[PDB]
Amino acid sequence: MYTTAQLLAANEQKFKFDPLFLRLFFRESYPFTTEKVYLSQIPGLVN
Amino acid sequence: QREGINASARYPKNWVTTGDPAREFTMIQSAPLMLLADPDEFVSVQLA
Amino acid sequence: MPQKWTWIPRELPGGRASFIHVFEPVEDGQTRGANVFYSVMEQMKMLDTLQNT
């Protein structure tokens, strides 16, 4: 009512967060139009 | 308030008292509220 | 292999145009040009199918 408070700077409390994976191991990003995706591994052991 | 220095860090002041004793003083006033924005930034540990 | 992006300014700080973009906008706020074939895509496709059949 008559306190005439003054505001100073406010701390932010930033969260600790860093991928290290998406930026390092997952360079390629692919979106889907289909409802499923297959993956193929070709076993090559030529005799 | 007379000198309009309501906001400051230090305020010297000298004056002499009336009457038979020629008594005069020296005086400095301050209101320090030294603070920090982040209380959790510093990590204090008592070693043992 | 991954498709990687890179950001390029249109002009250099000295004024040299780094990336020239040329097109003909049709209305205010347009950002990308449109090929003239949009209005006739279905006609062309269906006439190709017509000649084939």
Image (tube, coloured by chain):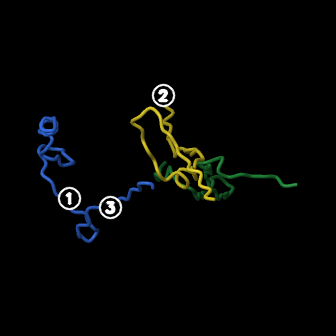
- Please state if A28 lies on the left or on the right of A46 as rendered: left
| Lateral position of residue A33 relative to residue C18, left or right | right
Looking at the picture, which amino acid does disc 3 mark?
Ile
Which residue is rendered at x = 42% and y = 41% of the image? A31
Graded by Cα atoms within 10 Å as few (under 14), some (14 to 19) or many (20 or more), the crowding at tag 2 reads: few
Number of marks: 3
The residue where tag 1 is placed is C21
Which residue carries the number 3 mark? Answer: C8
Single out the mark in the foreground, 2 or 3: 3
Q: Colour of chain C?
A: blue
* Camera-nearest residue between C39 and B26: C39
Please name the amino acid that badge 2 sits on: Met
Disc ID at residue A1: 2
- The residue drawn where x is 48% and y is 36% is A4
Q: CA distance from mark 2 to mark 3?
A: 55 Å
Identity of the residue furthest to the right in this view: B48
A41 left or right of C6 in image: right
